View: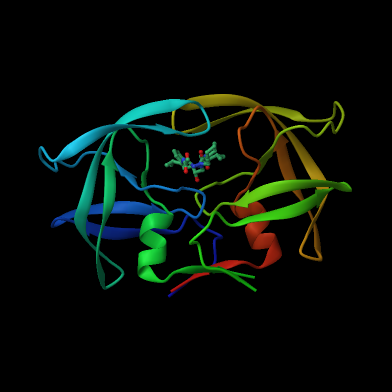
Length: 99
Length: 99
Ligand SMILES: CC(=O)N[C@H](C(=O)N[C@@H](Cc1ccccc1)[C@@H](O)CN(CC1CCCCC1)NC(=O)[C@@H](NC(C)=O)C(C)C)C(C)C
């Protein structure tokens, strides 16, 4: 699949079965999602962006189904306006940015 | 050429002749650079990301050179920790995200 970038590269992903719309983001080191419950196996983490920092709960080894691929990766939950799938997930998928 | 994403996709871009390191960012709608004084013909804007909003100054038709490609694009200056080339510049360069 090729994303031309004329529109936001958004797809539907399944995180432990829960469907979520995420943005494929090359400018994010991590993945952060809002609105899903993942349980008690987390450590609190601080993540910084353009307007400042935010607290998140970091879950490691979460099962993710996206673009017909299945991967286990770290996911953070927190107050984000858009669900982000950063490089930790993009590299696992084998996705690249081409010029 | 391709960016495999194991590392942040960073390049040296020349903006109106000045070299600057920028992050190629598919999760960004706009481009925001710090430390470039382009004059007073800009439009005041506000851009939001993780953590909140920042005030930016938008300039149109700015000369940008990346890996020997030259385009004129819209660019914003503002207090950003990292310089970002968002989708408006990535499309102008013909970049795409592939799997
Ligand atoms: C609306 C929009 O496109 N905002 C962009 C933006 O903040 N994009 C974020 C993801 C995003 C978009 C919209 C709403 C909320 C979040 C992302 O693509 C770019 N930023 C770049 C950061 C990098 C660290 C220094 C400051 C700039 N990435 C992040 O915020 C991520 N942080 C890190 C460290 O990777 C975070 C999502 C995990 C601006 C750069 C123009």
